[PDB]
Image 1 (cartoon, chains in turn blue, yellow):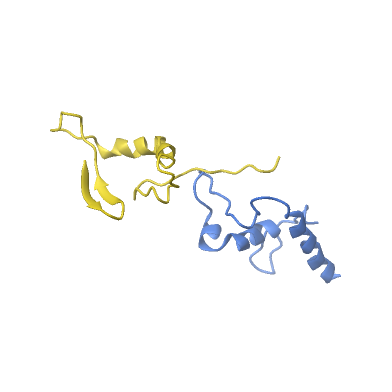
Image 2 (cartoon, helix red, strand yellow):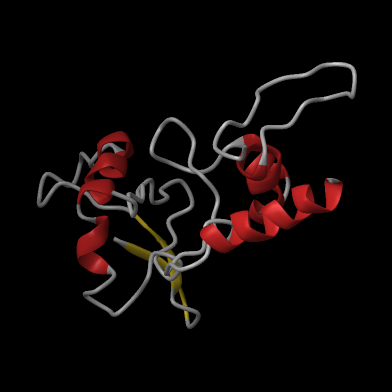
Length: 72
Length: 68
């Protein structure tokens, strides 16, 4: 069961392949057409694209957030 | 006006009035004046705005829209 969850994310990043500026390479901007958001400023753009991009993240295990319908 | 010429291509500058030299140009308008034609001068010396440093003026551009 849960390997196929990992296996789906292998294909998910493979869907996110094929392109000039790889999406994890750069930071998303802020809302002012200027520099970047805080978690892409405080940490690398490869991770930020994981806690919102790969999946929207929750803080704890006790709080269930977004369903990630396209990841479904 | 050119002051403190450094062989390292660095110097503090300001501009005046042409020959009403009793009065100078206020810097607050020069800051927006550079940001209008900032793109004009880097290719005037084959530069990249990381070789056009101004210390108070920085490029605020570049939103990408690659996917349809």
